[PDB]
Image (cartoon, chains in turn yellow, red):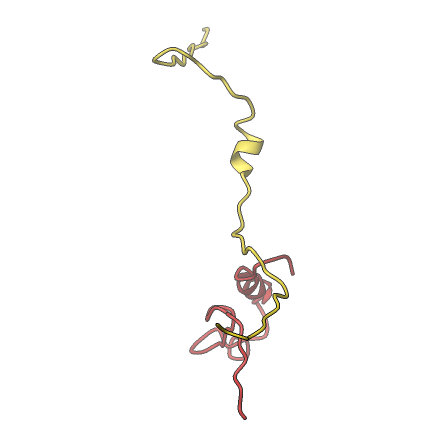
Length: 48
Length: 48
């Protein structure tokens, strides 16, 4: 149908800057849990 | 014959200073242009 010719030189996949700093520094460990709620506790610790 | 060749450069890449922020109206002291050049380079697609 068409007698044109074309050659492809180079293609790029542009990408947006992204680096998980806050996970990598502070939230270091994972805790998978199979239950339905998670409890986090504290203790006062003030002794006269 | 006049032929137009162009690539896709977003309008934010070609920056022209107008109004304030002229780099020649602010006083030559108490101002570091490092902030301006870092802000400009924030538009880049890779390390400069």
